[PDB]
Image: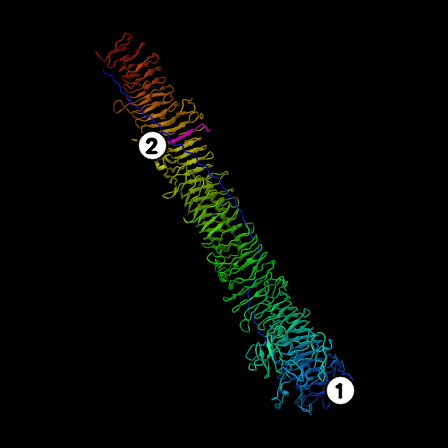
Amino acid sequence: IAITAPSAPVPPTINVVPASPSTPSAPTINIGIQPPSITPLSITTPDSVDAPNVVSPQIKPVDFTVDPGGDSNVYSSEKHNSHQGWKATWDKTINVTELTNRNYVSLTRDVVDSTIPDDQVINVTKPNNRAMVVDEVRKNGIKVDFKGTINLQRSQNVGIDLQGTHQGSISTPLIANIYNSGKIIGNAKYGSTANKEQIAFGFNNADGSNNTTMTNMVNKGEITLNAPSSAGIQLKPEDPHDWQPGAPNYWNAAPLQIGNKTPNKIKGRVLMKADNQKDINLNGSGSFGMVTVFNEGVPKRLFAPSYVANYENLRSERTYDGERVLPGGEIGRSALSDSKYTSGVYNTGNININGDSSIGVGLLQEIQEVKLAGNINIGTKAVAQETDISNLPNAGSKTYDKNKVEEAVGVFAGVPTMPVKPGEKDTLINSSGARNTATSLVGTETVEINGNISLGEHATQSIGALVGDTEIDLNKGQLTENGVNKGSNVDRKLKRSGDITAKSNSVINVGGKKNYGFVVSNSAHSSKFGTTVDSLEYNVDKTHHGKGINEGIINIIGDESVGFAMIKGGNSKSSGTISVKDNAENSIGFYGKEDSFTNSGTIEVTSAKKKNKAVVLDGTNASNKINFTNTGNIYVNTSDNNNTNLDGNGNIGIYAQGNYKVEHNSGIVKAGKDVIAFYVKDSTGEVNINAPIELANSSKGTTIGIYSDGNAKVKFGTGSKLKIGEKAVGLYSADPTKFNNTFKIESGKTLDVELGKNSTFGLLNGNNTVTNSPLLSKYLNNNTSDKINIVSFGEGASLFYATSKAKAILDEDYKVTNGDAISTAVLVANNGANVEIASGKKLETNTNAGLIAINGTVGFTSVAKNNGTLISTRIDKGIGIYTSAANGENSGTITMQNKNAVGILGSKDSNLKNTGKIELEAVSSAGVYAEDSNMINSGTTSEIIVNKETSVGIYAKETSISSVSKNVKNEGKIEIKADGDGKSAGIYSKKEGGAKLTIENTGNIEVAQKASAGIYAKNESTQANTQSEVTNSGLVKMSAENSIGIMGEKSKITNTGTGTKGIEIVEKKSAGILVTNESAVINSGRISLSNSSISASSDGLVGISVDGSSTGENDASGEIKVDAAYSTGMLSSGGGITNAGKIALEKKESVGMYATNANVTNSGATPKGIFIKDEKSVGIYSKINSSSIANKTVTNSGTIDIAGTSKTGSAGIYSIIESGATKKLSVVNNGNITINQKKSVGIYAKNESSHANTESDVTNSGKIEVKNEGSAGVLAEKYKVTNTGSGTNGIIVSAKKSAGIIGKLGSEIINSGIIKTEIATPTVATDGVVGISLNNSKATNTSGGVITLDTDYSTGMYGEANSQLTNEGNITGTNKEYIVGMAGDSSTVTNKNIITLNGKKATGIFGKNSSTLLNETTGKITTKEEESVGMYSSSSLKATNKGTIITEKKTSAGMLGDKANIENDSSITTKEEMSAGMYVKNG
């Protein structure tokens, strides 16, 4: 009968206020690029010389004189012909015998001129004779024309001859003109006997004749000689000793005996002139056509043993009666100035030389004049060479040819010509020594030719014009050579050498094979006589004798023939052209070895043909100590200074091997154009250059003083003033494998060279044959002054030029402080070559560009490796190295100083390999730059560093040019130790094409300046986040707050990171993944930031942040790890957010999903979603402020979980609106949200003012798992709560002492759905459940929500501390006893709605603790179960009742007393059985 009631426990309150982080700002970016254009230089390619062996055949004596037998005793013109000249009638078969028998026809002392008609044929039967002799015919100008046929058969025979006369006068020399139209032939065989010394015409005499004798001969017939060593026309000076026959017998004795010598002033000085006016054909070998023999006197045949003892030969200077005749012989001086008294040699006809090793025209004694204007042909007639026909049996030596003529010579010079000078005193000498004079110059100074001298096609290494010596012995006489009198002792040799001059009228048409055009094989033997008899003085004189004076054209119609070839002799004066008439090959002009010959003339290649070389200067062949004392006139192939032609190419100035050097030390030297002075070979050749040079600007090609294939010991030294202007090149090379040792440079030998424009140190191709890379690190090496300094440049020039698979190394440091404009870059790699940058190299620059690489023919992979310190300091756009179709590699340090500087750049489908360290200490600069190519960072030593703001690291662009994917790879560490709050980035990606780009980082990236991040990409156009997507398997770390982690456009990311891999952020305000244009992420890996000391309020971070153009979402395997306090996983701004992975919360004051001005979505469910572990936090929380314009909300369709049997201090759903902000922030629940923690709240919203709460909205269309005791469903302060859950959705309150709905003062409590208590009956009394609880506030139950009570002793609404409770909603509860909905403790209660209940002894209202009730009748209670009462009073001094009670159920009562005694006066109808309104529990 003692009915009591329990008491509800006190509910908790929560105040969680998490952090308010912010979104960081992406930095601005982008830098331009400039490409350089290289200068289009020129090329030249020489080669070497094979074998210019100059074998010079020697001269041989031709002393083949016949005895002057005089008249005959059977046909004397006096006793048999009556002095009427030639007798017209004779026998056609006269058998002429030798001179001893005198069977020859003789004609002497005639007054009638006679000749021979055509019909004659005469042979010779014996040697040493004349078929017929026409002697002593002065006749003062005889003139006839011979027409008979003459034949030669034995040796020492004469075809026909007309000799001079002993009668004449000094002032009127004789004039002659003889014609000879006949045929003369000298054959090669006499049975089986050899034939030689057969002479056609000539001059010879034993006894003296008249000096004033002057004669002329005109050739008119056919001349043929087939005996080897024959003689066409012979000229001789007469003996000044004037040897005489055996007087008084004289010429009667047979053979002649020379019986006396009569030297005299006016004896032995005759004059002679010869002329060929027809065809001379020489078939014999080693012969003479027209030669001036040496005046040796006579062979010993006329020297009897009685007179061999007093054999005083012309082997000494000869003086008689006061004469001063030079040793060896002399032709007298002429003063009557006319060509008809000019005694010498001249020709107009033709000479046909075909015998092997023969002489065209020979000079053996000094004569008055030698000028030649005829046809000198050697080897132009094909003949089958045979023994004693045109060759001789070999003497164990060189074999003579059968079809070609070899060792043949044309002009032979062993002595010069000595004409009459204007001051010269003539030889017009009277008997008493009375002598005339001359007032002018007659004849040319030396050997002269004005006619065509030609070598035939059969000419093989034959000689055109030979300047040789003449080695003749001498008697016991005085000797003097370059010093004191020798007093004999040293051998006495007739040292004689001649000199030749030529004119363009004399075309030297040398032809055939390797023929020796004009070889000065002499020794320049210039000889003079002293003040006494037998006096001789010798020197190397370059004025008097033995020189080379060239003025004429030397026509090289054959191939690889040589002209002026130098074995010995010293100097010569060159002023005439030597040219190749055709496309002949390897023609060499100068084979020089000795004293400085002077080139006072041009020597070039005036033809399209090339590969023929100019001058070979090497060690002296036949004189001591390589006499290259070259300081004379050196004027070759240049554009000025005594040589104004530069035509052709392949011209050389120096060619040498072995013992050679150059010694230019005085005067002036002028270098050629498109010609190279130096080119040498082998491995031991040294060069000395110390003379200052003068240069003119280079030609269409390129000019350089020095070149070699890389194999010379060329040296530089101070003193040689060097200069360049306008498109020349300092160092030229086509073969760098050996070039490394070419130029040794010694300290202090700094060379001063100044340059114009379009120039370059290194021109290199390598000929695709670079076996060895030249270690070129010496020319401006930093160690010592063993450098070369060529600094004076204009603008538009380069340093090194690499083509054709060449290779070279930057020396050390070199700079060109002469312009940063176009065509001024350090070096260019062309045709796909490779160059190496050694470590420690310091090619600093201020110019336009550094290294440029471009591929032509591939050959070898286009790549250059950097190991040195490469820095640029150009004022604007200083680019370090560039590659096109070429791979860039570095392993050293690269920095930069000035603005807009650029490091390594690649393009055109290549890759970039980084191994070195790059630091960005400058501004407005990018280290590695790329476009339409690949790249990679190789190894952790590949270090990318930034030291200042306004600079970016990796830069790669893509386009529509190639639609194949590229890649951006990193294996090194990118630690950015920069400054400033931003303005710096590490890796940057661009695209405009239709392809896709792969970007992955496996190495490390770090940033130490604020507001900066490494990854950032351009993927703006219409595509998903998988084309320029960035995936990470590397490490993303940081060192400065306010910064950013992941940045970019349209990318998909995974956290492939374990250990020291992934993303690590330990400081403030540095978001992990901020995204633009819809980027997604896989969060399976390390997001362990370890920030804010996980318990300290010192930092604040965000895992992933999003913008309006993006929706941030996590992979289903995503593991978003809260390793920091006051941090966040999801930051949302404008765009959308959705979770598909796992989102935990391990640290304090964090949030998985935080949203600003954006909507919140969850799809991750079963078993995905949000799983909160730590406390003082909420899984998802979004807030907006007065400044927030976006009307956004929060949605739930996933799993949000936090649980705890001892954890508390948190809430399920959180969202705040700041006071005064009418922005309508709301939350909707439709997912799973477990609240199994202690004292938590499913949905929380905080208020700051009593404003109109229509903006804040709280609806629960989903489910809340209230299974943990003591917690609360939802709390709010002056906000609107709508219980929109129905059935298993919404208010699932299933815990003991737990609370469904509680509100603060003036809270808008609304019920519009299910309100179902815990189904489980309490395990102990008073352990019921409460739905509504109040504390000095107001609550509004609404009938729109159904309130269901199933826990025993549970309550629907609860109130305390003067709380005013308003009831308007439905009340339901069944299957349990008591379960009073209304329990009150010290409060004012008003009832408005009618209450219904089920269960035994169910009661609607229960009052406790001095509580009082107004007792409104409308708040009545409907009784459904038996023994149920409506009112309950317990421990209440105040009680008011003014209404009747209607009972309609059995055992049901009205008023009920509890442990008290109060009496009143009221009556209530008890019409039903046992249904009365009153009963008492106390007696």
Distance CA(mark 2)–CA(mark 1)? 159 Å
Q: Which disc, if any, is residue 109? A: 1
| Left or right of 943 on screen, residue 242 | right
Mark 2, residue position = 1175
* The N terminus - image quarter: top left
Q: Residues within 10 Å of mark 2 (few under 14, many from 20)?
A: many
Judge by depth and name the residue closer to the eye, 1278 or 855. 1278
Q: Does the magenta stretch include residue 1188?
A: yes
**In the rendered view, how is the structure colored?**
rainbow
Q: Which amino acid does label 1 sit on?
A: Arg
Residue at x 62%, y 89% (from the top left corner): 307
Judge by depth and name the residue closer to the eye, 55 or 1007. 1007
Secondary structure found at label 2 = loop
Give the vertical position of 1343 relative to 1198 (above or below).
Answer: above
Judge by depth and name the residue closer to the eye, 1366 or 23. 23
Q: What stretch is highlighted in magenta?
A: 1179-1190
Give the vertical position of 690 relative to 1289 (above or below).
Answer: below
Q: Does the magenta stretch include residue 48?
A: no
Q: Which disc, if any, is residue 709? A: none
Give the vertical position of 1149 relative to 691 (above or below).
Answer: above
Q: Position of residue 1349 (x, y in %)?
A: 31, 21
Residue 40, picture quadrant: bottom right
* The C terminus - image quarter: top left
Q: Would you say the residues marked 2 and 1 are in contact, meaning their CB atoms lie under 8 Å apart? A: no
